[PDB]
Image (tube, rainbow, N blue to C red):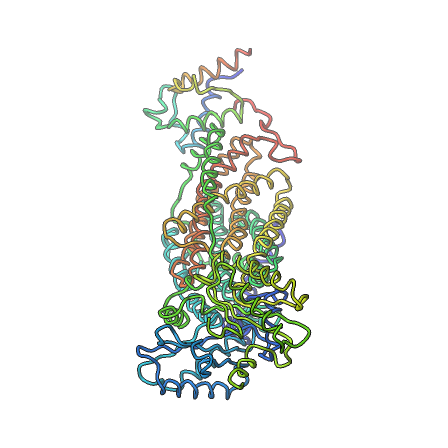
Amino acid sequence: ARPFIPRMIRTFAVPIILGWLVTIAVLNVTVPQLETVGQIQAVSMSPDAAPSMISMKHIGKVFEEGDSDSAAMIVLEGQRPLGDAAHAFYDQMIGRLQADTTHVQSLQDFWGDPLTATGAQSSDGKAAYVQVKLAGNQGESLANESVEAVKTIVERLAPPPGVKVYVTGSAALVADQQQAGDRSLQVIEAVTFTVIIVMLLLVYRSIITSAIMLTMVVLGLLATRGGVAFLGFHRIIGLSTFATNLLVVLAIAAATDYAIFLIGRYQEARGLGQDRESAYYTMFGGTAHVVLGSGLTIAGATFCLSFTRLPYFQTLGVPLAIGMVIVVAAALTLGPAIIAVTSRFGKLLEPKRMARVRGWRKVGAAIVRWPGPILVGAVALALVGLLTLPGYRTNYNDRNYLPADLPANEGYAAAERHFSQARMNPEVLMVESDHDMRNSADFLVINKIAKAIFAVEGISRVQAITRPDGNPDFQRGLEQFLSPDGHAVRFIISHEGDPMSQAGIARIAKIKTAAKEAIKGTPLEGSAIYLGGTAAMFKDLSDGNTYDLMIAGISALCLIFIIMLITTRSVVAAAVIVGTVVLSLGASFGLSVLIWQHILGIELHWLVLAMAVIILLAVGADYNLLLVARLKEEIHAGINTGIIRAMGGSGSVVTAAGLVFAFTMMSFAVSELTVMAQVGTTIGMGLLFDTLIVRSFMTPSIAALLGKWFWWPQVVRQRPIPQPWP
Amino acid sequence: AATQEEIIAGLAEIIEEVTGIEPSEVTPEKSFVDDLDIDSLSMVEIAVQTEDKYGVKIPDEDLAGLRTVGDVVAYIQKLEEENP
């Protein structure tokens, strides 16, 4: 007479265990590890449809300088003025670099030309720089391999005494970011496992139960990581460091939460004197649908996040959903079997102590007696956090979000010790015409254009054919400043101050407008204008970020509402569940902004809110869903008593789960990628606020205030047919 | 109508459900706070539970001065038997 699914799960537990173990072993043996797959299948950080990427590709194609947008810089630094031995070392290094052709596409020589000798010399003549163009776009495996090969080639020769060499640029920074992400992933896994061990031991006060929890969590994590690695091995999807870190941490935490829910329900059910079979059936029938709904909600939120335009969130989307689906399936199929097998052995999973049944009942009584002031105070507390909105300000450059011991940072510091910062990130402008510029009219036109460019405020230096620094000897510059066919010209732009702040980003439109105005009234009218550089690359991301955030955030609410409506079958309850979290977002945002920007003195990176909001909503909906599911069971005897009974019966479990999940997510502080620490801490405080105030003092108060209208369109009664005295 | 024994039995069941005290240890002479060790929130719980199951409206204003069980049952029978 028992339900079919739990009976079949209980009967065939051992084959289920054996099949899961065999599948995990096969997945972990056949395919390589997750880190190697992630390294092989990195994704480019700039969309292929961006104007900057197309412009830079055109720059490379017209001048026969390859096709990739990557670039690297080699810096020579010494404590004494450079000498002839330095020149010999430089030319032999240049020859050795030019010997290779698979990775080094091209390079420009300026220090070897007496006409442009001052272009690379410092003010005090103690440093020099050379630009080399690599193969492959930024952030993908080809660029990383090329920069590693360049470093290997440049290191194999012993430098002359008194000088040292460094490699800078964006590609080296991205490679160092990848390596730091891998090491941070290892350290984070270790720290998270330690925290889980200590917290479970503190909560349950039994070593065997904690060992069982860790068994389930480890099996689930191994299964999900093996599945994702196998899926990514066959070129199906792309990957990145952020996706891997989020997947691992979120899978561990979700598995822990599901195990806590199941075993807490089992122990509570058994505490009333029921036998083992009755407790097993009770926990299954009371928690299966809740667990399935929570898992589907998280998966749907991640898939909705996958509807963006930036490559990072696009790669974030699918693997997270696949991992969550695998984790939920593994939990639902493996938890009950392990629990039954262990419980059949006499004494393994017996309860130890009663946690709390009186305090939560008193809290429920206080809520029922005075709902109004409680709701008003909770709303005021939610709003005071959002009050600090107008102080928000974001940051863009990743140079100061990384440890200073990386080779790229050391090279940047060495360059800045003698040179200005903006000299390391130049801009390239191309003007393309339809004829040849070998007559005085075109040179004077170029002079006028250069003067107009220099007239713009915020441009430190301009380099052109007529001004190489701020007849074969003159013919040598033609090969470097004009196309071989003589149909286009290019200019080099060096900003003043930081070339990465908002002013630098805004200067691109101004300089393009100035160039367009200078073109007007000249025979070169109708010419093509192209710009290339880092600031141009970041401008497109700055433009698209807000639209991507809005489109990703709008659909998640609708999907969550639909899922909750399906699960609970009542419009008002789902609306309340969504609205409480929507209101509570502001307190978390304000608290994170206050902690990070004002006190620590570090602004927020532009990738934080997009990943934070979706996870916050998806996780925070589950606690309200569980509370509503319990209240629906307990309401049959009356709303006023039902609220008290539900609060007493499901008070401590949600608290333990919330603290465990928040403390697991707060372990990102040890990471050496400060973006990871920011995301983890923000989620931590947000969920602490959600589990301390919103879950316990807003939803029950709203339910008690609304009464029977909370379950529209279903019909319920408040006083159930009063009975005479016994 | 309602006799003393029925009201006492119902109240004892409510007390046993709420605070866990055995129903055989409640008499009208005993006191809620001095002897039975019952807090104000427990009184609110008792009032809510007895309002839902059977139906009696006891405002907190005159509930504050309600101390023993004898006055409780006297109030209950006054409200019930004397139908307004």
Residue A531 in which image quadrant: bottom right
Q: Nearer the viewer, residue A262 or A344?
A: A262
Q: Going 35% across and 28% down the picture, which residue do you hit?
A: B37
Residue A562 sits above or below residue A467 on the image: above
Q: Position of residue A57 (x, y in %)?
A: 61, 72
Q: Going 41% across and 34% down the picture, which residue do you hit?
A: B20
**From where the camera sits, is residue A73 visible?**
yes
Q: Position of residue A102 (x, y in %)?
A: 55, 84
Q: Nearer the viewer, residue A402 or A420?
A: A420
Q: Position of residue A619 (x, y in %)?
A: 52, 50
Total tally of numbered discs in the picture = 0
**From where the camera sits, is residue A215 visible?**
no
Residue A157 sits above or below residue A28 on the image: below
- In the displayed image of the protein, which residue is found farthest to the front? A440
Query: Left or right: where does residue B52 sit relative to residue A186?
Result: right
Residue A717 in which image quadrant: top right
